[PDB]
Amino acid sequence: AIERNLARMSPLVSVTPKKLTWEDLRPIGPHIYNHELPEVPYNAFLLMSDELGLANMTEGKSKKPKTLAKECLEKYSTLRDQTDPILIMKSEKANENFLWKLWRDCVNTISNEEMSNELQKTNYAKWATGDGLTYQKIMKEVAIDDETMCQEEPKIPNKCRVAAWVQTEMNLLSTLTSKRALDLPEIGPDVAPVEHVGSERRKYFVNEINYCKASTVMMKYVLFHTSLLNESNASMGKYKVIPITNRVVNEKGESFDMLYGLAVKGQSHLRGDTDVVTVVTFEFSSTDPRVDSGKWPKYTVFRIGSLFVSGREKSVYLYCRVNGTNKIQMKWGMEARRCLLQSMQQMEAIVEQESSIQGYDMTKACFKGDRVNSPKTFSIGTQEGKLVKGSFGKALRVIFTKCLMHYVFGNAQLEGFSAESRRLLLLIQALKDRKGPWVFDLEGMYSGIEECISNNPWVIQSAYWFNEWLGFEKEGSKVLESVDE
Amino acid sequence: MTLAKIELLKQLLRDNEAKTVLKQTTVDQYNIIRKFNTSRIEKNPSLRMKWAMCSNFPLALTKGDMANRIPLEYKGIQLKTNKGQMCSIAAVTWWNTYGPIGDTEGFERVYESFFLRKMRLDNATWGRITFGPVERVRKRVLLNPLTKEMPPDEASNVIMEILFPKEAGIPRESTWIHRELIKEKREKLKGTMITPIVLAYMLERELVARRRFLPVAGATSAEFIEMLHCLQGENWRQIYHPGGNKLTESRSQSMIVACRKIIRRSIVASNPLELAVEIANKTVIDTEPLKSCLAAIDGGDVACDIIRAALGLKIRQRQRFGRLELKRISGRGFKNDEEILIGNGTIQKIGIWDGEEEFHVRCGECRGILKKSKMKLEKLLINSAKKEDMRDLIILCMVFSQDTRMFQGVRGEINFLNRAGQLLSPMYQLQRYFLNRSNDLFDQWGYEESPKASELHGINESMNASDYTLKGVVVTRNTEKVSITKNLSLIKRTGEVIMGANDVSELESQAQLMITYDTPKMWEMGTTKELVQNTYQWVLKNLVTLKAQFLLGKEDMFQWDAFEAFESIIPQKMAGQYSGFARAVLKQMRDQEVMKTDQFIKLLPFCFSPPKLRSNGEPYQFLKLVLKGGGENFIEVRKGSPLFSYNPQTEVLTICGRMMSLKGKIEDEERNRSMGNAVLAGFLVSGKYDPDLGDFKTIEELEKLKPGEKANILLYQGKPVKVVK
Amino acid sequence: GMNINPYFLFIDVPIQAAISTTFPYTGVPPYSHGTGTGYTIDTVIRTHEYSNKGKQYISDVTGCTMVDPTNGPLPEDNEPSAYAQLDCVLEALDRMDEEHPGLFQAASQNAMETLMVTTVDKLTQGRQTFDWTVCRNQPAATALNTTITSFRLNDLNGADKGGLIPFCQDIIDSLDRPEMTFFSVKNIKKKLPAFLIKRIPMKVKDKITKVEYIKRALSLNTMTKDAERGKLKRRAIATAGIQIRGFVLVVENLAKNICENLEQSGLPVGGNEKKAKLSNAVAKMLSNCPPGGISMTVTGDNTKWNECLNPRIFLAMTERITRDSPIWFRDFCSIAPVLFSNKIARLGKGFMITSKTKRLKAQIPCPDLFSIPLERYNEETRAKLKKLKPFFNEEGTASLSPGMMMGMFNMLSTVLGVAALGIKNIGNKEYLWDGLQSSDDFALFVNAKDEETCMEGINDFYRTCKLLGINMSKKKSYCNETGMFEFTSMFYRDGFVSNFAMELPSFGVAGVNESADMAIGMTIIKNNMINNGMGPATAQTAIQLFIADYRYTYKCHRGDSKVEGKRMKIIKELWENTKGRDGLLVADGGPNIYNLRNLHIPEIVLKYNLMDPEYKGRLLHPQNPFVGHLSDYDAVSGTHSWRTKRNRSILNTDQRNMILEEQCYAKCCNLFEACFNSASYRKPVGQHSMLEAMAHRLRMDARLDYESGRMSKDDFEKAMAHLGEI
RNA sequence: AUCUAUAAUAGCCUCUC
RNA sequence: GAUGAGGCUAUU
RNA sequence: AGUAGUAACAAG
Ligand SMILES: *O[C@H]1[C@@H](O)[C@H](n2cnc3c(N)ncnc32)O[C@@H]1COP(=O)(O)OP(=O)(O)OP(=O)(O)OC[C@H]1O[C@@H](n2c[n+](C)c3c(=O)[nH]c(N)nc32)[C@H](O)[C@@H]1O
Ligand SMILES: [Mg+2]
Ligand SMILES: [Mg+2]
């Protein structure tokens, strides 16, 4: 039967095989290069590379969040006492007067002698937290009769182009700093030699990661989400000031409490997991929003003062933004430390491989080299169109930053893009290994990839990076086409 | 409290609804209403826990005197609600810090398995940690040790008898064997105030076995599976010595595996006897020398006897077939693969043993003499003993002989493969199959007149002596000194060979206990992939010196100990032909001055064995060189292979998944050199692929080509070329 | 300056070796909001579109619109097609049978025996199940009990026999009852000023006709799936009722029996066993490649796998497989595909229409979808409703004869896919194909002499799959030379590589309780070390991160720390009061002493010796109130095994009557367990009433106590009088 | 030689755009 | 409002 | 507003 049916089946029913060539691999998401579309704006919950933390030396005593903020503001009394605003940038639908009034209320509540971080439900606080904006539920019959009640047209994420601030964030978050934010707890003493090897390797790995800016940003996110979840459960019908706080340690062992701003929590009656609580964030920064205005459409910025870090003083602005979060986002932010693992396990694996090739532990050789082996280097980036190499620790930091951005900018768009681009990556790897890959519908796979590139900054930057790396791979393969030929 | 239960039942029966539920719900349907729940269970318990821990009183309290001991508040913190009382985690902490002090006997009793686990970990020694390739195989292994192991049904029956004898049901005969044990348990739990379900699950932990598919490498005993996470990874090994005691069966299996590995490594060496002795003297089974293990254990296989002879011990010609103890008396057998038709009609590949053999057979208490021939059980003389043991021994002997009747006596379902596709020993599968259904085997075997001699009497299938008995079986009322030769063959004083290296089984098995070799060349005892990776790593390490010797020297570079170890994983049939081919290819590469480093590295190890050329004086031509074990263990002459691949663009050599760099140890001009000059012996690239010659020629076509004639060759897809002799 | 490009890592590392970095599993998984009616309508429309060229008729039993694509015209293009040919399916099944003699017979015999020894309570093992009495979703046990009670109302007492066969016969007979009486839940609404509406549910008798009951029994409740990775758009899942689940079990058992003996099936093997089987198959295919030829691997997924598979083809499959079985078993196996052929899809909660200026919103339910003009719906919803009109039922449901709504016959679909893989050749052409199948995922290994012949074989396999109703995804499928591929999200590159990212979500706090969560986290770390290629340093870092997350979740930071909190003050006092501080648990502010070597030792056992006697006694108190007791039996677990009172108190709902039924059942079961101590450990067996068994047990207990001297004269007389009264 | 055997609940992973 | 199947894990 | 994304929350 099968033979007869195939005989009488139309030839148009075909898998249409097509041998894959480097030329057939075109850049993904061309629309990200046209300038008609706006550049993707900054939409992360908190500032990452533009964050400015007010540092107060601490004696190791975690007194309280409100007390910590009070001490930090007392140290920087000039910023705290700033009462007249100088508006630098304003969001399209924001009320700068109400935002400044809410900021002043937060500062006063934090600085007051009272031990409660509650804010009164004033007009400006009510506007900022979106009080009384839910639609009234009416009966089915009245709505059916009412001809003005129609199904709302869905809002689709808009299309944006590549923005340089994503590349700047990637560059800055993977650089080493002088502050350690990780607070890893102790483990049991090592007995087995494998445990000693693990501890010795952890020395290098944790030293590399802990000193990078991405680690501090991750710790800030984790702590803020923990505090926000606790406040949302505890204070459902209250407006609460939640300071954005972190704890860092200098290379000399001295600890500092860092205040990055203040957050206002709206009413938190989150019955469902996707129910939204509004958070109004006021974050200190040294970045002038006018250097690139396309990055801050969502932020109302006031210039609140100045600070001294060297002979030259630096301005201090207050980035104010209305934002939202749900219980799922808070829970997943409380456990962002897992990013570490995803970065370590990868690099760790590489080290292990080298050990198997050398007969001894190669962590020290990989990180810094030894008498017999030179340091291991990875293609890390481009400088004026030329490939650049970097150390093992630099690659580890880059992967950790990649995981952190997966968390920060993670949504359905990133998931779909990751899956489809993973398929394309497997095809590219098959091409590199001279396995003669074949495809059936390459345009379909490209359309699947590009359906997910709408406005996620990380997805757009990933498409740009994929295009650059694909061009470099084509250039490299051009030399592989003249072997035994 | 029977009267209290009766009163409670009456009070419940006062309620009309409870009355109708009790009257209309059957005992079978109880299991339904036990699960009756009005609301769906909340999802995402991680988020739910993170959310609830921020509440005031998320925990439920058990009303009683103990609950009332908890104060309403403690230093300004409300521990409990002032319906269902609820408390906060602070209440748990308060109880832990100021609560009443109770007795801890119940915890110690219930969790004795975990305390034994802790003791096993504590009384353990840790050896060195080695870095190198580790080949791990996924096998079904036991997770935790058990003093007594029974299947879940038997364990459940035993638990029911121990804890709930009243409502136990039918006294299954399968519990008979454990009756004594039950009493013991009923002695220990006579006055225990612990909830019966916790004790039942303690008993299940102590009895029921948990077997899982895990990746292991050389240590499958449950004591080693507990530490599996620390024993090894994919690139490192950790020597571990668990505490406690180990079974004799595990030691016997481990020493059998060790002896087989030692013999396999030694046979390919010059003077195999000396190398075998040297390796055996440095072998340790877990934490005991191999020599001591061989001396102590009364058993083993051919390899164990060979190693005993090499070490100066006395050979023990003993064999185990699950529940049989067979001691050789005379005769020699040879195992040959053959396709046998089973009674079910499915053909199976089985290793049939030929020749005539005499065995002293023991099983439990039953003893006998077994006279066996090829595919036929000739005779079996038995002495009176326990009837059950007698019949079990009879059926075990019948299955062992591989008689045609036994193969034809199968009527049912037999699984010779597991769910993972791994092969199961057909002989043991048949033994297990016929152990529980010996009636069909006896019926198919046949019967004959019972012997009428003075001391010879037969036995029928009815479990008793009778005038009718199954063919062959007859009831009756009634050390060797050898020298091992150079090639690991044992010979009697008369000179007849009783054992040899070829008689050692080629099956690769995972030792139950960890085996160590206190020699720098321990890696030579590894699997095929580990040996290949280590050999190629060594070749890469000494690449410059090997190149220098090759360009200056002619044949001295082909002899090394690393290549000797590599030769053990090349099947002996193809070793000489591979060596001839590789030597010819390397010589042609050197003489013609067209040298490719990647191919030189790939083919150098194969040049160790003495060459074996064709009858016409030319070497064999190959497309791939196959290695022992698995279908993925081969080296491709032209293209890459799962074990060996080269990337000229990046100049990266991938060996068994590990990437190494040839940068520096390479000449860029080699990228402009053709691969066609280093794929066939005596062939050199003549020019472009000429369509006139036609289709590409095969290996057999190449071998028959006369000297000086061209041929079209496909190095790999999209890269044709024409070569000449 | 220098710009970081993470993709440049792939220049130094192959994609498979660094595949873990391509999974963004540290981010939040997608969730669905609001109604799933749009997705359900889209699924219905697509399922009917892929079969619109088949025979359309009107069901004589329910009056629904039925579409039959089987034996329909062959596809003329590459669009998804449900026009499977019965002859080709039977030929593939015959090929499978003759490659595997006795496989179908053995599978049917095993399934028959399992069904013969299967009880009704097996139906309580599912999750949320559609309840027809309330037309809602209820726990599987609740739905089963409600169905049993309703059947008892309608003179259907098969469930009393205990076996599943009498219960399924009862379902079949219930399909014939001219009228059905049952118990339903009705809500009384009260005005609580704040005004809010308070709902009080209560049980009331209700009656429906034969046709309504038949449609309800065939109905599938549809909802939206949440927390799904790798997908841009949300999708709809469905759940069936008790009637369908009663028969799906035997078909699934038969299909599993078949699949377990097929070397091309990726099911039911999973994990390490699946990895071993796949590696063995790949090695066998590599060794079997003809000399001098080429072997090519196709990584493929099937597009519209569920929409295009037809229940009629599954009925034919069941008939073919159970060829040598007794008639009753053949009918029993045929029931489930018959039910799926006449399935009805419930379209969900409906849609929401809003007035932006007036700030109003209202939920139009599925029955009233067409009560408003289609112009008041948005563009996509309007088009979907227009296309749905022909298959719409006036009661708010849709006719969905074609397709399988969601993964109910995974094993049978795998059998069909493997049968497709078993042809291996078309027209004696010079190629041979084999492969591995797991539901819609497959890997096809084609051995030939050149690449063109391999492509011809792949095309032949594609067309053969088209003949069987299987549509290979040309967009998501690709091929290369054998040695590298992907299957079921497992990446093979000269061996299967470790994918650590997929395990990341399991590294958090489980959310059971303090001690259970500690054990689960340690065991997760250990198992990821064993299986997912996690190194010792990464394992120790995971231990540290789990300890930090655990302390922050349970507010049990170190005792010497200065952290503030209600629990922390008591933790500090305990830390001050304790001498053997190393013996304190992490939940009690004690130090963490876990490392790689002791990941398998429970925390209490690990610290048992180091505990101070007073703290040890307090923690392991047999009568501690935080763990439920039996009733006073001793509990050996510590105070940290507490339970959270999961009160699913839906806002503005007061269950003053349904909780009463729950409590009545709980009291009855508790008394039964008190009378029968082994009930919890072992499932009690018996076709008699619980009351009779309990009465006889109590009578025996009283008599034996009297004979042994445990009970005196007066108490024995009272017990006998009470028993006689009962 | 683990092939057999295996109660329930919960979690994590994998499998229409 | 959160389904089916498979694997693994913890507990009773 | 905002979160967010084919449909919801912005209390009931
Ligand atoms: O687990 C494997 C092996 O280690 C184990 N085994 C074998 N011998 C022992 C002892 N003595 N102690 C503990 N464990 C032991 O049994 C498994 C056998 O694996 P494998 O190497 O594949 O077995 P072999 O290749 O020897 O063939 P097999 O049929 O399985 O026989 C195993 C065992 O039985 C002997 N034997 C059976 N028959 C029918 C034999 C025969 O006809 N002639 C001879 N000479 N021997 C026969 C084998 O020789 C072995 O003793
Ligand atoms: Mg799929
Ligand atoms: Mg796939």
Image: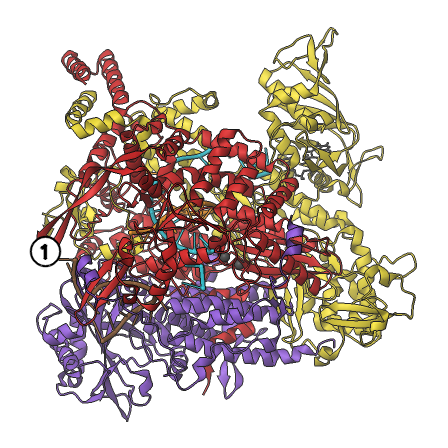
Chain colours: A purple, B yellow, C red, D cyan, E orange, F brown
In the figure, residue C153 lies in which quadrant?
A: top left
Q: Is mark 1 within 8 Å of ligand 2?
A: no
Q: Amino acid under label 1?
A: Gly
Mark 1 closeness class: few <14, some 14–19, many ≥20 residues within 10 Å: few
* SS state under label 1: loop
Q: Is residue C358 visible?
A: yes
In the figure, residue C130 lies in which quadrant?
A: top left
Q: Residue at x 80, y 60 (%)?
A: B579
Q: Position of residue C538 (x, y in %)?
A: 44, 62
Badge 1: chain ID = B
Q: Mark 1 highlights which residue?
A: B76
Q: Residue at x 33, y 44 (%)?
A: C129
Q: Residue at x 84, y 74 (%)?
A: B591
Q: Position of residue C579 (x, y in %)?
A: 24, 51
In the figure, is residue B148 to the left or right of B558? left
Q: Quadrant of the C terminus of chain A?
A: bottom right
Q: How many marks?
A: 1
Q: Is residue C269 visible?
A: no
In the figure, is residue C720 to the left or right of C147? left
Q: Is B723 situated above or below C415? A: below
Q: Position of residue B446 (x, y in %)?
A: 70, 17
Relative depth, front residue between A326 and C709: A326
In the figure, is residue B325 to the left or right of A280? right
Relative depth, front residue between B723 and B475: B723
Relative depth, front residue between B660 and B188: B660
In the figure, is residue B297 to the left or right of A63? right
Q: Residue furthest bottom?
A: A311
Q: Is A38 situated above or below C79? A: below
Q: Position of residue B108 (x, y in %)?
A: 33, 37
Relative depth, front residue between B422 and C614: B422
